[PDB]
Each structure stands twice: as C-alpha cells, then as structure tokens.
Image (cartoon, coloured by chain):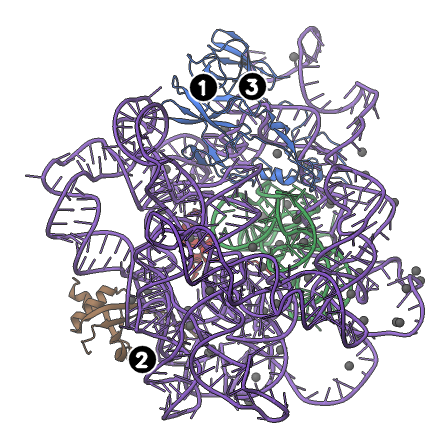
Chain colours: A blue, B brown, C red, D green, E purple
Amino acid sequence: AVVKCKPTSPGRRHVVKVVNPELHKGKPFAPLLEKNSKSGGRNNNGRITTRHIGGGHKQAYRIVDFKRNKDGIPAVVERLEYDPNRSANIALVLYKDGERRYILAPKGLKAGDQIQSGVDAAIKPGNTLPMRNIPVGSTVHNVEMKPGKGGQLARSAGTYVQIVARDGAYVTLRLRSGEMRKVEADCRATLGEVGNAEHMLRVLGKAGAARWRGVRPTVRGTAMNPVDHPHGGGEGRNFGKHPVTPWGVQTKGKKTRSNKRTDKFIVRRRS
Amino acid sequence: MIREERLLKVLRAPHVSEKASTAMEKSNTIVLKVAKDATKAEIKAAVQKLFEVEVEVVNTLVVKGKVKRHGQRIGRRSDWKKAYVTLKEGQNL
Amino acid sequence: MKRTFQPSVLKRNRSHGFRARMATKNGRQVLARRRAKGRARLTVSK
RNA sequence: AGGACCGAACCGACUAAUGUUGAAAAAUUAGCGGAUGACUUGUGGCUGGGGGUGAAAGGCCAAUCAAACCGGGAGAUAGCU
RNA sequence: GCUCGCCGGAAGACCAAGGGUUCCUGUCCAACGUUAAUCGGGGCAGGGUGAGUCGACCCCUAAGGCGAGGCCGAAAGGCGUAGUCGAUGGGAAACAGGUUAAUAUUCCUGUACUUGGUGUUACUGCGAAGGGGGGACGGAGAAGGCUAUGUUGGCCGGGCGACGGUUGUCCCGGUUUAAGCGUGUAGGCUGGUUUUCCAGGCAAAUCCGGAAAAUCAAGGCUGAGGCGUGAUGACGAGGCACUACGGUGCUGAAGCAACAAAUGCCCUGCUUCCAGGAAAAGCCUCUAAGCAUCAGGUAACAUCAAAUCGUACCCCAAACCGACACAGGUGGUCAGGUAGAGAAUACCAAGGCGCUUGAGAGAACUCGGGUGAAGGAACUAGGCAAAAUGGUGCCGUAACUUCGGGAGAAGGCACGCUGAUAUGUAGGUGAGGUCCCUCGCGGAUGGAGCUGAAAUCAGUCGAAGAUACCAGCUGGCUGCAACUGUUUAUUAAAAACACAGCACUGUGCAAACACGAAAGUGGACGUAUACGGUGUGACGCCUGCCCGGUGCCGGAAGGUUAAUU
Ligand SMILES: [Mg+2]
Ligand SMILES: [Mg+2]
Ligand SMILES: [Mg+2]
Ligand SMILES: [Mg+2]
Ligand SMILES: [Mg+2]
Ligand SMILES: [Mg+2]
Ligand SMILES: [Mg+2]
Ligand SMILES: [Mg+2]
Ligand SMILES: [Mg+2]
Ligand SMILES: [Mg+2]
Ligand SMILES: [Mg+2]
Ligand SMILES: [Mg+2]
Ligand SMILES: [Mg+2]
Ligand SMILES: [Mg+2]
Ligand SMILES: [Mg+2]
Ligand SMILES: [Mg+2]
Ligand SMILES: [Mg+2]
Ligand SMILES: [Mg+2]
Ligand SMILES: [Mg+2]
Ligand SMILES: [Mg+2]
Ligand SMILES: [Mg+2]
Ligand SMILES: [Mg+2]
Ligand SMILES: [Mg+2]
Ligand SMILES: [Mg+2]
Ligand SMILES: [Mg+2]
Ligand SMILES: [Mg+2]
Ligand SMILES: [Mg+2]
Ligand SMILES: [Mg+2]
Ligand SMILES: [Mg+2]
Ligand SMILES: [Mg+2]
Ligand SMILES: [Mg+2]
Ligand SMILES: [Mg+2]
Ligand SMILES: [Mg+2]
Ligand SMILES: [Mg+2]
Ligand SMILES: [Mg+2]
Ligand SMILES: [Mg+2]
Ligand SMILES: [Mg+2]
Ligand SMILES: [Mg+2]
Ligand SMILES: [Mg+2]
Ligand SMILES: [Mg+2]
Ligand SMILES: [Mg+2]
Ligand SMILES: [Mg+2]
Ligand SMILES: [Mg+2]
Ligand SMILES: [Mg+2]
Ligand SMILES: [Mg+2]
Ligand SMILES: [Mg+2]
Ligand SMILES: [Mg+2]
Ligand SMILES: [Mg+2]
Ligand SMILES: [Mg+2]
Ligand SMILES: [Mg+2]
Ligand SMILES: [Mg+2]
Ligand SMILES: [Mg+2]
Ligand SMILES: [Mg+2]
Ligand SMILES: [Mg+2]
C-alpha cells in the first residue's frame, strides 16, 4: 500500500512510502546469494565513466533465474521477498523435485500458488511458455531476445509486454516504451505483469533518501565555469547557447541510436 | 643430531655482568654470547657437548648495536645474540 | 596543525620501495640513473 | 519514529579582541554551528597533469595550481631595463 | 625535608602508528639547554629488551594488485583466465602472586591450558582439487538479569588528641584473592523420533533438500552471573630487629554482610524499521576414484616438539608530524569520592606537575580583568563590544499554520535549614522461619534488616536559598532562500552549490553515454515504474502570445555537388 508520513519534521513532510505487509521479514535464502561490491561509476581504468554514483546501503545479490529452464517439474511459491537490486519483488519457489529458485514475482502471485514452465504449462500467471504457444493478445513479462538466453525485457515493476501478432518464425511485441519489435517465436515469456506496480508512487521526500540509494548530487552545467562545461560562464545568470552534454553534443532532441545490425527487427520506433 | 663443526661454531663467548652473575647464583643460569644465526636447539646441544653440563631450557634475545661516534664520524656496532640457558639444578658450572 | 608528511612505513615501501621500483622499466630507469650518479641509497628501502 | 529538539565528547569556523620580525608561514582567548546523520573517524586501496577529482569557489591534486613537481630542448626569445 | 599552589574524562595510566637507545648506572659541563647549572632527552663509558599460550610470522580471504597461457597494441606496453598475493576482517591455547637500577601474562613460585607428531592397546570403513552445513555479519529501540565499582554496617589492629570538649550514636586504617575445573542458573531458540519414497545438490552419497505414515510428546543447542574447588595457599594494617637512612630481614589479626549500580556482560539475544545489511578458511558432515585380513578413523596411555623474529624507552608528546625543548596536530583502552541529569561544571583521591631567566619599582601608554554617582544608545556605518537572560516543578501562553508547529511564545509563583506527619513515609530490596514437590542455582508463604524519594504543615536564619561554578535575552515589521546540508584549506558561509519535487530529451540492450588507437570496462549481473543528459527547484495558485532568426526533428520532388569513370 501507499502511505504518506506525518509532518513531524521537515525531512518527513513529503515522504510517501510503499508498504507491503506480505513480504517476508527474515533473511533471504543463503545458498542463492552473492556479494557484489560497489563501483562508484568507475571502470577498470579507475575513471568515472558514469557520473552521480556512489555510497548507498550495502547490498547482497540474489541469484534470480531469468531463464526458467526447469521444464515439467511443478513449483510452489514459498514466499515473496524484498530484493535491493531491482524495483520488482521476487518470489522463492519450491520445485516438486526439491530445488528452490528465485523468480521475478508477477502481479497477484501469492504464497502457495503453482507455477510451471514449458510447452505443456497452462496459460496462467507465472507460467513460462514459448511465445509460439502463447495466444495472440496475451500480456507477458520477462521476455527473451534469443531462445535460451533468458528474459531481458519487461523486468521492472509494473511493466509488461503485449503480443500483437505472429507471422512465421517471428512474433511482434509492443514494448513498454511504445516500440514495435520483432522477436523469434521460440523465445520464452512469462504470463502476467511484473508486480509491485505501485513502486512509482513513492516520494523520496529528502536528499538523504536519494543518497541511501547510491545517487550522488547532480551539478548543473550552467552553474560552473566555461573551462569545465560548455554551459559555464556569465556575470550573473547567463545561458545564450544551445543545450549540450558535458562533451558538446546537443542534448534536446538529437537522436543517438546508430545500430545497423538491428534496424531490421524494429517495426516502428516508439515515436 | 647436529654436526660437531656447527656445535663448535655456535658458541661465541660467555656474557659477564651483574645480571648474568645474579642469574648464575640465583636461577642456575649462565648467559652466553652466541651466533646471530643460532637456534635454541643448537645452543642446547652445544652447551651439552662442549660444557659437559645438562640443559633444560634456552631463552634467547637479540641485542641491537649502538650508534657511536669516533672523531666526529658516524659509526654503529653489530647486533649480536644473547642466550640464557637454565641448567638442571645439579650441574654447578 | 596537520602537516603534509604523515609517515607510514608500509605505504612508503609500497610507493617508493626497491621492489616497487623494479616492477616497471621507468622505475628501473630511476635505479639506473641513481646508480650512475653514485647514490649510496638507491631507494627508501634502506 | 525523526537528514526531530537542548546539550558534552567529536566535527566545524559566524563575531570580536590579541597577535602581525607571532607561541603559530592561519593560531590563542571569550562567545558561535552541527552533534543518529547527505554524520564522523582509523587502516589499506584506486583515479595523474590539458589529466584527475570537484553538493561548482576556477576549488583541491604534498605550505606550489586559469594548467603540479623534477629533469631535459636550453645559453628559448627579450626592438626592454 | 617541611609548607604553598595547579591538573585530575587529565596536565593520571596503558597501547597502536611513528621514532630508534631518547631507558638504567657512573662520570664531565667545552659546545647544546633562550639565564646559572653541581642538573639534563647534552658529551663519554658500562649495562639493559628472556614467550608453546602476547604480536608478527602462519592458515584464509576484502578492496585492490600482479598475472602461465590468452585477447589487443608502431615499439614501449594495455587488459585479463587459471592462479597467486593483499588486513583495516575470520582462524588453537595462561592466570594470580613475587622479583631488577633498568624486562616480564616472557624470569621465579603455585596452579593450568592448546596443537601436532611418534609408539603400545582396544574397537573399526577410510578416503577429495567434489556435495551440504556452519563460520556469517544492518540501523534503531526496550526491558529484565548481572558484574565491574562504590557506600555503609559488622569485625580486626591502632588512638584518647598542641586551644573549650571528645569511653563514644568517637576518630584512623585494613577488610584482597585469578585462570582452570565442577555445577547448567536468570534467559534465548528449536517440536523430537523411527521407518519408507524421490526429475533436486555436474558422479555418488546414509549427508542436504522434498514427500508420506507411525508414535511420542519431552528431547536438543545456547547462556552472563552465583556457588564449590582452585586456596591448610598467597596477600594483608600493624608489629620486632638491621640501615649504607635509599631500603633489608621476620611475623602477620580480621579478611564478613547489606544496599546502590553502569555506556561493560548475558546480547552475534529480543522487538521493530527499510535504506534489506563481506568473503574464504579453520570446524562438522557425506561420499567419488583409490585402498580394502594394509592403510586410514575413534578412544585410552606414554613420550617428544612448539622454531624464527619483536619485546628497552616516548607515545595528546621536550622522543611522532609542525626548520625549535614550537600555546598547533595525532587513532584506540581504563574511568574513584562529594555535589550534579551528566564523560558538563566546582573541589578532591590514585597519580602527576609549578610550564629552563630572575630580582625590584608601583610613571605615561598597551594588554587581560573588577567596580562606578546622575543619565541610559545621546556612541557608532551598525548596540561592534560589553551589560543582560539563564535551573527544576507548577499555573499560563497570541497572530498565523502545510494542523506537525509557532512554543521554552510571552508572563508568573515556589525553592535554604529544622521538626512533625512517619523515632524513616510511598516505594525498592529482601534474610530467617515455615510449607509443597518431578529435591534443586526449585516453587508458595513470609516478612527481620538495609535502602529511600516526593509532599503538606509548623517553625527558623539572612539583604539575598535555581545564592558559587554552571546556565535561553525577549517581542514586532519586512527582503532572500522552502527546509537538514555544501563551498572559496589561508581576507567572501551567502541571496551562491546541492536538495526532495517537476519538465523536456536521448536510450530496445552487444542500449544511449563515458574511459579506452584496441582488447576491454563502467552503465548493470540493471532492462523504459530502467539508465544518461539538460534546465527548474518543497508546497500552494499557476506558467500567456511569437517557429520570422538560430538550433534540433521529419521529408525528398526540383536545383547544386566529392572521390570515381
Ligand atoms: Mg546522472
Ligand atoms: Mg535533478
Ligand atoms: Mg561560479
Ligand atoms: Mg569550452
Ligand atoms: Mg545580468
Ligand atoms: Mg541576453
Ligand atoms: Mg538533529
Ligand atoms: Mg571546511
Ligand atoms: Mg571566515
Ligand atoms: Mg573557540
Ligand atoms: Mg539543531
Ligand atoms: Mg546541539
Ligand atoms: Mg568567477
Ligand atoms: Mg597546496
Ligand atoms: Mg599551458
Ligand atoms: Mg633549441
Ligand atoms: Mg637566458
Ligand atoms: Mg575537567
Ligand atoms: Mg645517544
Ligand atoms: Mg648556559
Ligand atoms: Mg661557568
Ligand atoms: Mg633519563
Ligand atoms: Mg644522556
Ligand atoms: Mg622471543
Ligand atoms: Mg618459558
Ligand atoms: Mg603472457
Ligand atoms: Mg592485469
Ligand atoms: Mg594467500
Ligand atoms: Mg589484521
Ligand atoms: Mg618498565
Ligand atoms: Mg561487588
Ligand atoms: Mg553511548
Ligand atoms: Mg615495556
Ligand atoms: Mg619549555
Ligand atoms: Mg608542543
Ligand atoms: Mg582529533
Ligand atoms: Mg619559560
Ligand atoms: Mg599597574
Ligand atoms: Mg585596563
Ligand atoms: Mg563590569
Ligand atoms: Mg554608571
Ligand atoms: Mg546607579
Ligand atoms: Mg532604563
Ligand atoms: Mg544615534
Ligand atoms: Mg552622532
Ligand atoms: Mg554582540
Ligand atoms: Mg557578557
Ligand atoms: Mg527592500
Ligand atoms: Mg538555505
Ligand atoms: Mg577564505
Ligand atoms: Mg556491456
Ligand atoms: Mg535556480
Ligand atoms: Mg513561457
Ligand atoms: Mg539527395
């Protein structure tokens, strides 16, 4: 649910939280965990290559099965869990054969529900089938680019993909961005949407909350000197130039996609 | 079992001082100058061979040489090794 | 007040030591130059 | 509960006086701000000079910064003193 | 040596880092020490650092580094796999007393513990470069049980007081004891157990995970402290004798109890919150190959080993960083008494110091302070500076407000000491004695003793009772910035930066973008409820007209046009 805090202090007045009483409160499943230390936007050269990244809370990586390649064996939702690494919630499923896996938790899937993957799985939320066997018009998430590669589309909270058409070896997908993209029919998908749709109603409320998520402050280019931004300079507040990136590229409307390898797979750009 | 040449080489000289004397009268302990590369087992064996006494335990420390001056010139002495060996309360050396 | 030299033997050795010098050909150029001049102390090691 | 309140440690540095061949190449004394947080601190590590880093002052990068330091081109050039 | 003063959350004590003989003894005063120096961190010489348990080394990993092959690159080199290094983290084990001029958890005394190796015996499925478990982890908050420690009473030794009094409801001092072992308590968590079945754990597995019956319902893991022992012990005021007047030798009484109580322990616990909280080894366990009347595993005993290196001394400082014996800087640990909420503050204890020129005088003037007639901001750029306020409990408190605030608004009253209530109250603690039982660190009853607020009433001293130190000035109107934060280290702290929020725009994932001649890497083990760039800057009401100029987006008819031919 979505609850706003009482204004008992200036840093609390505008905080809007998303509360989920259903999420598990204990520690996550230990054998499905890994460490991932923070980079702070630095690459192997040690240079900042993405700005505004640093700090935040320590996080453990939950190994999430994006492929869903356990065909036939039924599985039951043991619980729903909080994952720091992504905006979506995850679910711990127990397979009939005794194996436990983390999956992306779809909308509406509670504890005790049955899920199944494969051609023989039914048309039910949380079930993973080839898009060849998924009917036209269905709403899916965790969509594959290439067969066997794993879901790479519609993975964040409240996101889904609709199957608009099927012609031969390819189905058409209307992506969340508004783009029409062609995908091989053998690529898998999971029925239903991604849960936690009310993720985007949260209001951070204060600067520190954004600092907790490892986001460092952004400085406007017009607030600095010309030696370190094209926007720099001026006695007082002056702009008089076309807005650009810190590296001189026009940053309002100039298209930057240039990939001739994959233009054939785009039916229609998002526009 | 240590070669006899090594044993004849590991004992340098006996240390004489008020502390060495008091150890000798009270705790039946002789204090010796030994090679910088001498171990406790070698000290024990050499004292049992060349002194004909019986040892029960060896204690070792390394003394650092002093920085001195000779005619307004910097100069330093060598870091040597000192051993306390406890004799078995009947040896009388 | 806090001055610029805050000594640490480990960091001194890792930045300017003999093995740190020998790790690169430019450090070896440093050693070669200091040998040619006749320096009694090639590195911070001793 | 809280980038909540008063207030020591701790981190700072708003006012005044002193000091200005100082006790000190930035401090002392009396007041002052924060003090569970975007806090502070130890140890070790990474980013290198038209480069780094910068909650952005052209700030900081070993008392040096609108282009560090050391060596070299080099006895640069100087219609100037 | 006797007085005086200063610190005492330090200006005491013990470490780490850093330094390197500055430590101790003798000797000297040339130079060094801001003066003298017989003194010294100065000169010179001699001495001093004792470990199976502390630390390193060692085993294991983090960030990161290096990196056989490999990929890439004019050369130099870059990156990176397998590996191998890398603590600031994980991993076995010792306490108390005594002792030197200088070392001690290292030496001695007493009493312990760990690991490993060999051999004898007994039983016996062992075996990993593999599987599983464990190690193993956040913030805040609350309570109970304790201890460290303190106070008092009892007891034991001593005293009867320089000047009125002091055989007492008097004064002074002591009243200490460890690890280890045994006990398994206050407390925390977990339902046991036996069979059978199995797409899972790369192969297997009795191990782990999953499923199903039966049966029991009590078993297991963890755990401060207390008690017993350790301990007929050591220690202990005091006393007796030597003294080289520094100290040496001998003995040694009591050595109990109650109350108070931590920020330390139970506690890596419990509760709750979101921002969701290392790794790997040691350790347990299982099998694979292999070995299978041998090896190998378990237990008893015995013996042997535990190396090497560090250990002095300073360590908020005269020994480290600041050129100095420099009002500076420097991480961790201990934490007594009265008053106090307190690690504030004042005075003290333990302990440590009087800051390496002094002696006079008592001019102007400077600096740091105290007081001031009458006036009260008239000063001045400006109340700068100073003065002033200042605690606890209760009564009481406006506009406006985003309903939280404003607010400690403003303002006001009481406050000491003594007696009574009540020879010490409410409460807290809590023995005996007794009673019950699965008999013990049990339950129930009980209340001796100890401890002890707050209040009312009466009385009483002073000019003054929040009496010292300590410790908000208050109110009104208005600009700017929503707010907490950040910044010109060293003349600017702000209205500047950031901010939560908003909008535009890019980006379909081998993403855009960034660092890289490249390989690669970050973005991100993320996937449009995501990520980058730009502008604006909580919130409320809102954001109007212009596409001519210049950008950017879309288009492709007609003109122009490169290499080419
Ligand atoms: Mg950004
Ligand atoms: Mg922004
Ligand atoms: Mg500016
Ligand atoms: Mg420019
Ligand atoms: Mg202007
Ligand atoms: Mg203009
Ligand atoms: Mg606060
Ligand atoms: Mg600052
Ligand atoms: Mg200033
Ligand atoms: Mg101050
Ligand atoms: Mg405040
Ligand atoms: Mg405060
Ligand atoms: Mg400027
Ligand atoms: Mg500088
Ligand atoms: Mg230049
Ligand atoms: Mg030239
Ligand atoms: Mg010249
Ligand atoms: Mg004090
Ligand atoms: Mg000396
Ligand atoms: Mg002199
Ligand atoms: Mg003289
Ligand atoms: Mg001395
Ligand atoms: Mg001396
Ligand atoms: Mg040793
Ligand atoms: Mg020993
Ligand atoms: Mg190679
Ligand atoms: Mg490499
Ligand atoms: Mg290693
Ligand atoms: Mg370490
Ligand atoms: Mg000592
Ligand atoms: Mg006690
Ligand atoms: Mg505390
Ligand atoms: Mg010592
Ligand atoms: Mg001095
Ligand atoms: Mg000083
Ligand atoms: Mg400090
Ligand atoms: Mg002086
Ligand atoms: Mg005077
Ligand atoms: Mg005056
Ligand atoms: Mg006055
Ligand atoms: Mg007056
Ligand atoms: Mg008057
Ligand atoms: Mg008046
Ligand atoms: Mg006036
Ligand atoms: Mg005037
Ligand atoms: Mg003032
Ligand atoms: Mg004042
Ligand atoms: Mg105005
Ligand atoms: Mg502001
Ligand atoms: Mg400044
Ligand atoms: Mg990539
Ligand atoms: Mg602005
Ligand atoms: Mg407009
Ligand atoms: Mg054309």
Q: Dot 2 falls on which chain?
A: B
Q: Secondary structure at mark 2?
A: loop
Residue A115, disc: 1
| Identity, as a three-letter code, of the amino acid under mark 1 | Ile
Q: Quadrant of residue E372?
A: bottom right
Residue B17, disc: 2
Q: Which of E342 and A55 lies nearest the eye of the viewer?
A: E342
Q: Are marks 1 and 3 on the same chain?
A: yes
Q: Secondary structure at mark 3?
A: loop
Which residue is labeled 3 in the image? A160
Q: Is residue E447 above or below residue B34?
A: above
- Residue name at image x 54 percent, y 19 percent: A193
Within 10 Å of disc 2 (Cα), the crowding (few <14, some 14-19, many 20+) is: few
- Residue name at image x 17 percent, y 72 percent: B50
Q: Is residue B83 above or below residue E489?
A: below
Circle 3 or circle 2, nearest the eye: 3
Within 10 Å of disc 3 (Cα), the crowding (few <14, some 14-19, many 20+) is: many
Alpha carbons under labels 3 and 2: distance apart: 90 Å
Q: Are marks 3 and 2 on the same chain?
A: no
Q: Which of E373 and E105 lies nearest the eye of the viewer?
A: E373
Q: Going from the N terminus, do you reach mark 1 or mark 3 first?
A: 1
